[PDB]
Image: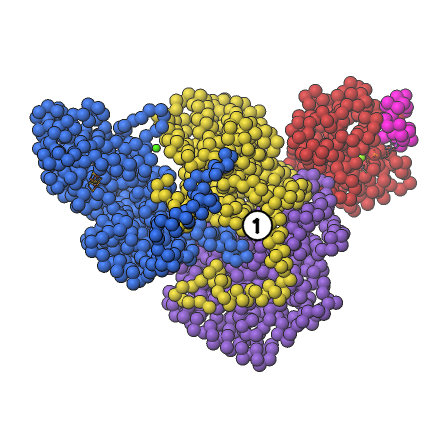
Chain colours: A red, B yellow, C blue, D purple
Amino acid sequence: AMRQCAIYGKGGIGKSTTTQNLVAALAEMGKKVMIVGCDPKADSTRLILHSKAQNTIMEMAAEAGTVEDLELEDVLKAGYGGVKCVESGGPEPGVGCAGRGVITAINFLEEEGAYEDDLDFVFYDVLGDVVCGGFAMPIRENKAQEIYIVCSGEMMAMYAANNISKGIVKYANSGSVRLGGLICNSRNTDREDELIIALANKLGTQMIHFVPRDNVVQRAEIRRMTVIEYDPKAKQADEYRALARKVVDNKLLVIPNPITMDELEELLMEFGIM
Amino acid sequence: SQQVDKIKASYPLFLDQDYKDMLAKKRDGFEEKYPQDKIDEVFQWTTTKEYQELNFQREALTVNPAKACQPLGAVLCALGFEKTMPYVHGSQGCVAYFRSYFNRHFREPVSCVSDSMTEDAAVFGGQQNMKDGLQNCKATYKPDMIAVSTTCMAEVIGDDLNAFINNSKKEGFIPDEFPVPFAHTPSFVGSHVTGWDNMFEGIARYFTLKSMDDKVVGSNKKINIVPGFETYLGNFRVIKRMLSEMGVGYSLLSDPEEVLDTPADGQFRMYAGGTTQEEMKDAPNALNTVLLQPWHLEKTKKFVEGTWKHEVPKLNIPMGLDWTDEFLMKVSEISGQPIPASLTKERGRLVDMMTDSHTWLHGKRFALWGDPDFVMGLVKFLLELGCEPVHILCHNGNKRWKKAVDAILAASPYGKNATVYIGKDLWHLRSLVFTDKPDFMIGNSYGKFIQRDTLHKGKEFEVPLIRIGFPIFDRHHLHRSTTLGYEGAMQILTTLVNSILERLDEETRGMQATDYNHDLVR
Amino acid sequence: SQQVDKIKASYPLFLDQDYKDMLAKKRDGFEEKYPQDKIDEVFQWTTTKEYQELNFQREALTVNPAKACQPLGAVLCALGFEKTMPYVHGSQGCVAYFRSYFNRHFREPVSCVSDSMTEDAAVFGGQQNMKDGLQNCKATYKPDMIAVSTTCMAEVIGDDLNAFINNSKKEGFIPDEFPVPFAHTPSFVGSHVTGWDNMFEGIARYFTLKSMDDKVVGSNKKINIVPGFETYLGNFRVIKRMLSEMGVGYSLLSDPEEVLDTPADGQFRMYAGGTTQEEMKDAPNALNTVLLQPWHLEKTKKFVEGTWKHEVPKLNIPMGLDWTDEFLMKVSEISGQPIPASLTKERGRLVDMMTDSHTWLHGKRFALWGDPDFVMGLVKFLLELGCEPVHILCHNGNKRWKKAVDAILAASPYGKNATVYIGKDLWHLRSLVFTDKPDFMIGNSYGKFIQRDTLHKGKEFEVPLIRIGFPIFDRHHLHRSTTLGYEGAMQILTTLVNSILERLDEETRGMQATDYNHDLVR
Amino acid sequence: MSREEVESLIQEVLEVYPEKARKDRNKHLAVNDPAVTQSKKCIISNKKSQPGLMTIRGCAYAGSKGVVWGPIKDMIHISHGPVGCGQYSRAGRRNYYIGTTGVNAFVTMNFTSDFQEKDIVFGGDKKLAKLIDEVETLFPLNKGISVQSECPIGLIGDDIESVSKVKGAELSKTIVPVRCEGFRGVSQSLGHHIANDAVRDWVLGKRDEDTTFASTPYDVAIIGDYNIGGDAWSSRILLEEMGLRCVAQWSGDGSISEIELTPKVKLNLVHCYRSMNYISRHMEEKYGIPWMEYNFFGPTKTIESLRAIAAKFDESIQKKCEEVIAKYKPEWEAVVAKYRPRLEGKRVMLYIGGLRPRHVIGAYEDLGMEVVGTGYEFAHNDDYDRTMKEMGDSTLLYDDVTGYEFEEFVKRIKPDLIGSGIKEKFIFQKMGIPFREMHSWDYSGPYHGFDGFAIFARDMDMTLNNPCWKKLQAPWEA
Ligand SMILES: Nc1ncnc2c1ncn2[C@@H]1O[C@H](COP(=O)(O)OP(=O)(O)O)[C@@H](O)[C@H]1O
Ligand code: CFM
Ligand code: CLF
Ligand code: CLF
Ligand code: SF4
Ligand code: ALF
Ligand SMILES: [Ca+2]
Ligand SMILES: [Ca+2]
Ligand SMILES: [Mg+2]
């Protein structure tokens, strides 16, 4: 048991929202989960904690003097479905270095043994712009074993997806991390499903699932909760339940096969028009 | 001018009248310096309690620190392994500094390499530098191992050392089986000693973590010893000597005494002696592991207990009388070997020296600083001697350590006026030796500037420095000394008393003034 | 007055105003002392070449000699034999001084006995004192042997020691087989080193002269080592270590290292270690005999070659680099043992230190004194370091020795300005350091008074004292040092370079005056 | 001897490097030749160091804070970033000054922000602001502050110039932000440039509108002399003896006010071209002040320089110049008569930074010694162009030499003496080769001017002819 996963993808593509909803589904199935927020903005746990967490590791460590004076209990909180939540934390936009904060945060979790023995899953929710080594911390040796890239039929999102695939290769070749697949978080573009499927095939992976764009997500979000909690009978709620199962039973873990910019342009022209 | 028969270097030379005249004109014409009255006024001010309070209120400014950064320690630790080349991933300016810092203390050659990451490597990452770097080092300096540590630059950008090394191997830059242990050594975390601790744990993990299956505790009948950051050659030697004298099988893990003391015989040896690879791989089979300086071997301890399953004894550094005794008795209990008549005699000789010199050492107030374990050892020994440590400063100390030092101080009547300061620097200590004058101060060469300042206030205010610690740059070959064991205690004791007697002779050398007390027999 | 919290001993105390006023009243009112102007005038005069010339024309007056009398040496020699009680036939006042002289240098107990010859014993001879003396000693202190030496009173009156001891046995005051070796040690002939030589030769004869028949040179495969008058426990220790390191069987005849360094463990040991009687009796069987300080082992040599038939090698004291080399090469040739890698590395390390410190030592001028062998060993080492010995004084040296030293001096470019003096004292040396000022002087504690006199003329005239020799009374535990071998050379080199750097530090400590040269690194 | 053998030696040495490094290093080793006026056809310099080859090079920080700024007496220099850079470089360079350390002078002290993890993660500009306030309180006599950026400051993008401007205006003080992040450039060299630019941008123009300074036709400024062991002072006494008035010395015993007065001088005398050509060129284009390089190492060079300098003024100065030369003639002649016979014909190999490799050659030759090999840690090609004329033919030249290369070169060439840095000193001494530190002068008196030549000669002799060099081999080992 105990599977660690990292979620990556285009900025604002919906990874923090999808993760929390996917996790709420998992807890519904009776799975024990921890979500590790790896983004300066400590917003990867609001729908689960029903509030913006304030006890972030970095801020908590700055107060206690050093991370060495910190303690799990102070930063690790349980929310909906018994889901465990921790937030790396970081500086306000435009100052400091958020990457280093993530390195420090992850090591602290590692050394405090947060990654407990009876967890079924651990999800690292990473920001969209992996602009440095610090944000690859989740996929170093003995961390996440599977990666899921969230994207959409949008040209720029698919480019970010391929681009990230390139960055994964160094880590996948030196370790055991593998790309588990692409999660299409639909944005109503034309022939969107064909686009993602073609890119997945080119990368050598699969389109795990296709989450539809549904404003119910926004209404649930406004009330600080996932769709599974907000409205269990919602059609979208079942979409996440299906995503959860696809994840749980997934056995396809490969090493990204990055394509060139030209190959990507050629792919957009072929499956993008009409 | 110069007299070819008696040439003058800068010191005597610039005291010649023409040079004095010149410097006087330089000052008055273009330096726009503050009047001498203002300078003296401000000087006096910096010696008061009012200034001291402002001084201790500092929150952002550090002045004259008593510590170095992590990588310095990682390098020293790597030098302790056979044919190992310290490799620092990051900027080359660092390595240039680590080498010359050590060159100056040991006055020996210090081999260390860098992969010179520049502007574009800080941007795109330092993986290429690692691939070409490991290949170039191996081919050029033919080491049998490359111990990798980091500069702050590589730490900020989170360069993945493990992934770079693994890919360097996967791509043929170096053989798959070539040992390349590594450690993340943040210049902004801890101090040089933390670097030593991280580097060592990283080396122990590389040779041991994946191969614990066949290991059995106590099977090789030896005792592992981890010295920690040590810059006194005599400390490595006295430990080996005492164990061998007890007929105790031991394995010193990280032993740089040979590379730091090669003979000048017409041949340069980049590598010498050092802890072998086989010794490290076999370490888990030892009966137990002893950590000589526990306060900066915290990470190592956690690894040795969790992975090796050794019940690491709770021992203080073997300095002074009581802690050396405790060390020996523990080693005897772990190895079964009795403490020999030899060591019993050595202990008795130290006690003899203590009794012979106690009247001169009694009540003498000292200010001292250094690394955690060292400083605590000195405090403990000082107390046994009947001395009064009054200002104890450890810049890289922490709260727990301070709590332990306070307990050692409270257990003795001689610790009544002592205070322990952590996170304070030599400018703070400067204030303390003015407002609460000690007879002497014990520390590294950086304290010479403090002795300089105190004398400026007046001869009666001068606080002589007693050179013990790291680094020592203004005296020669003091790195050959010993501070551990009875031997070390004997050396420290001789130095303290004779320093005291020296100063006494200086104060009473005045003829028909103070020489009435210039006794031939002390 | 006194403040109970900060009590003042004589030094700070008599500087208080009231004491000063009182001392002033005492001076002007009843001392009738010469005006200060007159005192300063005569002091200046005593530092001139004119005064020096008068000083050196002394024929009858000796001031501040640098030597002691024979029995002092006899006593040290005896203490080197197992359970032997030094016994000085003569007046008790002698023994009181011998014991307190050694007490103050070793800061250890020194057991010596006297038969207390008073007025009537002087007149009627001291045969009874010997009879009752030998019996009281043997019964009270239970020695295994009593080595008898003499006071000058007993030498003037010609007390026959042999006769007195023989009758002591014949009449039953002490068993006929109890060993009682003896020696005539007149105060008015030679010095303390002569007494060591006479006492040793006396003990060697007692155990060897009458039993030469069954002796075969080289049958025990050992080498005898005669240390001579030695006051550094480290010297005995390094010699033992070097031979054992070479796996050379040896026998040190007269070894007091244990009695002069017993442990303080709640028990007083009057006797410890020492050369056993068996070792002396079997001595003629060794391959050869080496004399560590030949220049004062003249009588011992004559006996060793004439009676033991040993071909004593012509070796100089093993001090410095070259002479330690020669000493090892000679032992290797005599014993057949090659010089081990261990020692070759040690030598290389001495050379490393020499190269690391040569720039601070080059051209430094030294005035020095002590015993013949020691003094010569120092001169040699100084020359090897590129130093300039300028005033070499040996109060108890002779014409032959002087010639030999002048030979060593001419063999080196660094001996150009050196002058050797024999039969001269410390008041003569004092003039030399004023008229031809050296940078430092190396000698025993009596030199401290010369440093005091030089500083009185001015700081720029002060000649600092580096303590090396015998006796050393104002510093503690220096008697544990080592001057022989590479170890001693390393220790001496360390003391010289750091004395130079200490003085340099003192001179450049003046802020905004000389501190421009107060470098952190030297 | 013979470039044929030297070129072969170079090839033999390169045989151990992997292809990539071999090809690169090959461009940095050459056999000198007196006629080439353009060194880019012989050697390339000022390029990145190959990774893992153990070079001797430092960083931009050492170049900025270590050589250019740290010397300045009455300013407080803050090593901004983790403790470390500042600790290793504390009082390691013997740039001598006159002052009361801790009150009006701070050269020998180490001021730092001692960055901890939260300073990197959350930025340190607020810490920098508070640090400046603490400095103003505890050190009221400081006449200015500089903040020398260490590696991390360059990565996280702290806005030091903003803090400098703001606090600067608030306290009415000159606060100079220097972006000398270690990883910038490839050596100490870019740090010199960054340092010069910071002087130009934040200090030099301060008195552009002021005319209260009373100048004379003989005002000069010595720039590029860091007063190592007092080198600048023994140079200054010569210039003032021939009638010139030194209004400023750049960074050796230098004060901020004399830097601000430099734009008023008639001539800028540059000793270290590598580190100070930048500001010299700026003062010429902006203030019209001409500059000229000089060399005070040894009598032939010193006399040549005094005459060339004197020629820039009138006859009264030239007359005094000859008077100065006549005065010292007996003195240096006595130095050569005594030491040349002891040093005559001995061969030397040098390896230093960016000036001395070429500048000290004349002094060596003044003692009859020959420089068989020379090289620089971080010189540019304009430096090598000036080097080919100074070196003899078929001599060896090396740029940013590696440990392995230097060692192997010394083994074959077998020089009688080596002049380099502290990182090389103990290797060669073990090999039994006399070594002299040519950076710190091995803690010995000044080497500039006539008074320094005597100490220079005594030092070279003291070390080269020392008796220890004969004892390296144990007697029992042929
Ligand atoms: N399936 C969906 N349907 C509708 N809106 C969605 C969906 N997924 C995400 N969103 C919206 O997109 C916004 C940003 O997504 P977020 O979870 O922050 O992703 P990222 O972590 O990549 O920024 C959310 O505020 C939410 O309104
Ligand atoms: S290695 Fe000078 S360009 Fe610069 S510190 Fe030494 S050969 Fe420097 S002369 Fe100078 S005072 Fe220097 S000696 Fe130019 S200042 S970066 Mo290391
Ligand atoms: S009882 Fe008293 S101390 Fe003894 S001798 Fe007589 S007066 Fe003098 Fe002098 S020289 Fe040495 S110590 Fe003696 S053996 Fe002669
Ligand atoms: S290239 Fe130069 S010296 Fe190196 S860091 Fe950068 S400016 Fe400074 Fe500083 S603290 Fe220690 S020594 Fe380095 S790891 Fe950081
Ligand atoms: S890109 Fe990353 S390593 Fe660089 S300063 Fe920003 S958060 Fe830090
Ligand atoms: F803007 Al994001 F994950 F919050 F890419
Ligand atoms: Ca050395
Ligand atoms: Ca004693
Ligand atoms: Mg997000």
As drawn, the residue found furthest toward the top would be A30
Task: Tell whether C421 sits left or right of A249.
Answer: left
- Residue plotted at (76% across, 25% down): A77
* Image quadrant in which you'd find residue D255: bottom right
- Residue plotted at (69% across, 27% down): A71
Residue D209: image x %, image y %? 75, 67
Q: Which residues are magenta?
A: A208-235
Residue C282: image x %, image y %? 17, 32
Task: Tell whether C46 sits left or right of B504.
Answer: left
Q: Is residue D327 magenta?
A: no
Residue A14: image x %, image y %? 83, 34
In this orientation, which residue lies closer to the viewer: C371 or C361?
Answer: C371
* Image quadrant in which you'd find residue C39: bottom left
To which residue does mark 1 refer? Answer: D90
> Secondary structure under badge 1?
loop
- Residue plotted at (19% across, 46% down): C190
In this orientation, which residue lies closer to the viewer: D65 or A206?
Answer: D65
In this orientation, which residue lies closer to the viewer: B441 or C473?
Answer: C473
Amino acid type shown at disc 1? Arg
Residue B214 shows in this picture: no
* Image quadrant in which you'd find residue C223: top left
Q: Within 10 angstroms of label 1, few (less than 14), some, or many (20 or more) residues?
A: some
Q: Is residue D247 above or below residue C71?
A: below
